[PDB]
Image (cartoon, grey):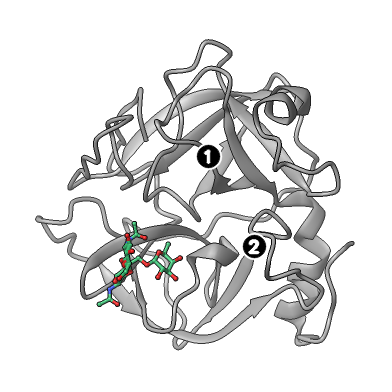
Amino acid sequence: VIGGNECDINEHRFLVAFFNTTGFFCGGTLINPEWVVTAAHCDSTDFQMQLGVHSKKVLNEDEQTRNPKEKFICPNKNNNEVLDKDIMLIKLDKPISNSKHIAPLSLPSSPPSVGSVCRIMGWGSITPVKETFPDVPYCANINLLDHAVCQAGYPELLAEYRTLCAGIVQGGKDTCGGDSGGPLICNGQFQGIVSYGAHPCGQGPKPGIYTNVFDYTDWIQRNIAGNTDATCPP
Ligand SMILES: *[C@@H]1O[C@H](CO[C@@H]2O[C@@H](C)[C@@H](O)[C@@H](O)[C@@H]2O)[C@@H](O[C@@H]2O[C@H](CO)[C@@H](O)[C@H](O)[C@H]2NC(C)=O)[C@H](O)[C@H]1NC(C)=O
């Protein structure tokens, strides 16, 4: 995250860190005791999740480690299009209980509104060109922009992809390398998933692209109910 500051230690209880033995590589959102939502492109053959984390060096007392018991991506997703249905559901190998630094964030109940103020967060790079990874997660506020802005900046962004466009018109505040999979929270609602962006990060003509969570809520709920055979909207 660039153009921001260190997050408050209590404002990201739902933030999940994805890591392997090399380090953190993605973020995720705890939506209930046994489920985490992240980006499909954050999938890997071997990884674990750390909950209740703030600083990588100073352990939080209630920090928990979890493994992916089951993973779900849209059955009708085209694997050759990284921007097509970039969302993945993960069932934990063991449920977690609410604690000082751990609590779920509910699925959105209302669609995103252009012009709303949104917050981004993650352990991604805090510098635009060079890669500088912080020990603590950084936070920043940005605006939900008209989809036309991203359309003009990204020739690869097709109209059929269910995405949201966010940042500020002049650039300078944006997600960066390593923030993928994290939540985009607008008006207190989990509205998007960090999905795609450009490098250098924070270019005015190239705002961040986030997966529209609202559109996948029904699919998500059916998988949680036990209908892991459900398909995503075209
Ligand atoms: C730990 O994971 C990192 C990153 O994994 C990749 O990126 C994730 C977002 C997700 O898409 C995964 O499926 C990817 O594999 C690995 O680091 C990458 O390693 C490759 C080659 O080894 C390198 O080209 C990339 O630049 C690295 N990171 C980036 C920028 O993506 C790392 O190898 C994994 N550690 C182990 C031991 O498995």
Residue occupied by mark 2: 87
Mark 1 closeness class: few <14, some 14–19, many ≥20 residues within 10 Å: many
Q: Provide residue 231's location: percent of width, then percent of height.
A: 85, 75
Q: Quadrant of residue 112?
A: top right
Identified by mark 2, the residue type is Ile
Instruction: Confirm whether residue 129 shows in the render.
Output: yes
Mark 1 or mark 2, which is nearer to you? Answer: 1
* The N terminus: image quadrant: top left
Q: Residue at x 82, y 74 (%)?
A: 76
Instruction: Confirm whether residue 189 shows in the render.
Output: no
Residue occupied by mark 1: 197
Q: Provide residue 180's location: percent of width, then percent of height.
A: 47, 52
Lateral position of residue 147 relative to residue 13, left or right:
right
Lateral position of residue 56 relative to residue 119, left or right:
left
Query: Residue extending furthest right?
Result: 234
Identified by mark 1, the residue type is Gly
Q: Provide residue 164's location: percent of width, then percent of height.
A: 70, 38
Q: Residue at x 27, y 58 (%)?
A: 53
Q: Secondary structure at mark 1?
A: loop
Query: Residue extending furthest top?
Result: 170
Q: Is residue 18 above or below residue 207?
A: below
Q: Provide residue 40's location: percent of width, then percent of height.
A: 59, 66
Q: Is residue 16 above or below residue 55?
A: below
Mark 2 closeness class: few <14, some 14–19, many ≥20 residues within 10 Å: many
Q: Secondary structure at mark 2?
A: loop
Query: Residue extending furthest left?
Result: 57
